[PDB]
Structures are given as structure tokens and as C-alpha cells.
Length: 112
Image (cartoon, rainbow, N blue to C red):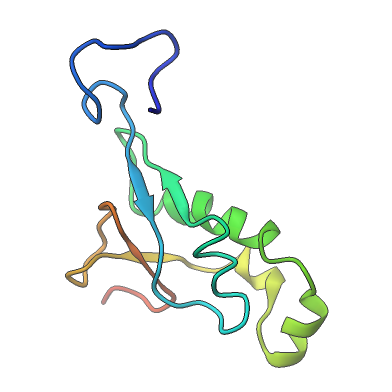
């Protein structure tokens, strides 16, 4: 119930609270995949936000959340330092840049 500062029972949720709920479950890793999908893949979306704004708030935690043994990732090919400076294209269930209840995390661009 992500309600504003001082507010409660004003009319309904997802209308006044000015927030939402979105999850990520597409593809990123092979060993530490659940670390960013199960450990914490849920995030809140304000009222006025862009699909690109979440690419800086969602990918963030994905870093500190997946920093168990970067020494290995870098040895396999997966860079942890790049994740913080990489592009996060949030896709939908239709194949577009949407931020619905569930948005996929694709590395490749939309089409541009």
C-alpha cells in the first residue's frame, strides 16, 4: 500500500496512492538469475514516469544484489561493472516498451 505521505482511505488504490507494482522475469544470467528475479525483482512505479526511468532504478539494485563473487562473472564473460553502465530496455508481453504489472528486461534495443 504505497500511499502518499499522510493519506488513507480517500477513494481507492492504484488511483490516489500515485504508484504501481511491476516485476521482471525475462533473462539476464544463468547462475545468478533468481538473484535478480526472486531475491528482489519487484519494484514500484510512480504516477508520472518513463520506461527509461526504471532502467536506472531497477538495474541499480540488480548490481548490489548480484555482487557475491564478481571475480567469477568476469571470468565467465559477465561483467558487473557494465551492468551499472548498461542499457535496460523494459519490454512487455506484446513486445513493446511498457511498464505493466510485468515487464521483461531485454538488453537489445526496441527498434530505433
